[PDB]
Length: 577
Image (tube, rainbow, N blue to C red; front, side, top):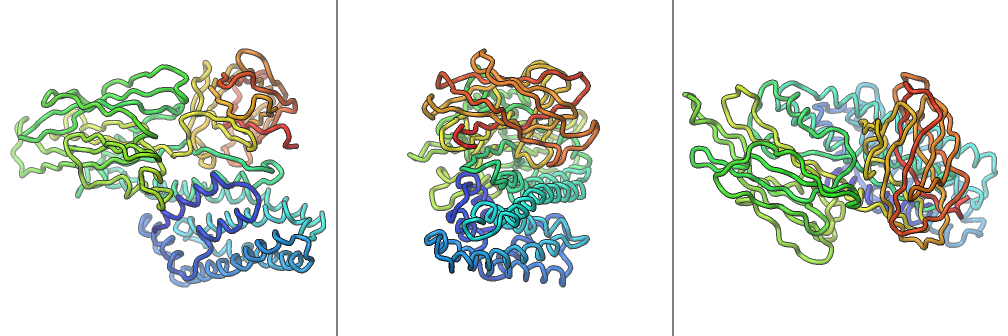
């Protein structure tokens, strides 16, 4: 198991078991920290060193691995003490131990951390910094909750919660600043650079950004109970270009521009693939996709045809079944040639096959084969989050969209390189609001946008993209399914940024429900950082009248020309005060 396999399972844990307790505490031991030896840490460092091409200087490299082993042994002491204390929480002995162990844990973290942010080696240390920072917020969150019951005085507990608050933000900002710096250091003009650039973005989303997005949930006073997030960002693969022995000069810009722009989240319904021929070689020449709005709250639309519809063989219909497409086994075809080219005998850089497999927890589903299988497996770059069940059940992402990159007009060869888009399994097909948890629903999971609302690129720490609007109006509208008894009262919070004070109004099924004044959070022309956002609630609770409702959100009472950014809304049970 690699840094990518560990990280994916950690993310699964953090998305399903985010509640203060022993289980959380021991959870972090079984997944990451219950390890002995540099081995895993050296593996975490190598994974990024060999990507940005920067091996950390020896001394610093060893010192960093050493602190990691130190934090590992100590947390193992801490976790055991906590397990015992929670069992006999009154035993003054156990309660003094926890205060002893806590302090040591905390001070070790405060010291190890800067050594994981060594000058000039900030980028390759990055996944190891994120793992420590995650541990730290976790322990600060620990006193903040059980400090009194351990015997701490309200004054220290209050200072710890203040540290937890300052750091949740400091850590978030550091990770995003360095991720963005390596990412640009890796960019280049030719296609070889794009493959490296995209690979950095891909792996660092899986091992850094996906963790950072959950840092906000450590704020114990804001998320007292089980809170549940959803990651809506997309990661990409391009079989034809990632497996090519060479490099098409100056093609990077083209490749990026081909990636679908910020948009509301949609569910893939089908792909109809078209086959052409050249020199006795059939290949995937073009295709057409059809997708539905989240929750299928709208009708199935279709995108224009990507590529060209060839006649060489009849169209193949790939239609969604099960929990989606969790695997693609691609077959790239590189027909190279020793020059002499009138427009006729040409080089081919395309795919002549791909097997699509459908996810399921119950049964083994029949895949849909387009011509033949291949050896380029998606699982090798986007692995299961759970390796104790077949990949069909432990899959971490599901296919969302397939573009089609082609050769520039005037290029003398045939390039048919489709970029595949992958969606995190957490972004559920439906928006479900149950009881006994603070359900988070990002606004990209909206059924539709209001006039003038834009889906803008996320800042890096929100787990996906965010909506924006510069004048009073309706933001968006979303279908919601309540599994909790309708008797349940809820309250809504809105994580947002705004250069102005304004009102947010909500309405369920046309009926006005909440309204309130929210204030500004940033100066005009400031660049978004964790501080720019605020998560504010409405005081008045409400009930849902029906199982499936249409929730609408709008902003008012402000001059146009101001930027308003809205990330997500949270449905908090009324009993949580």
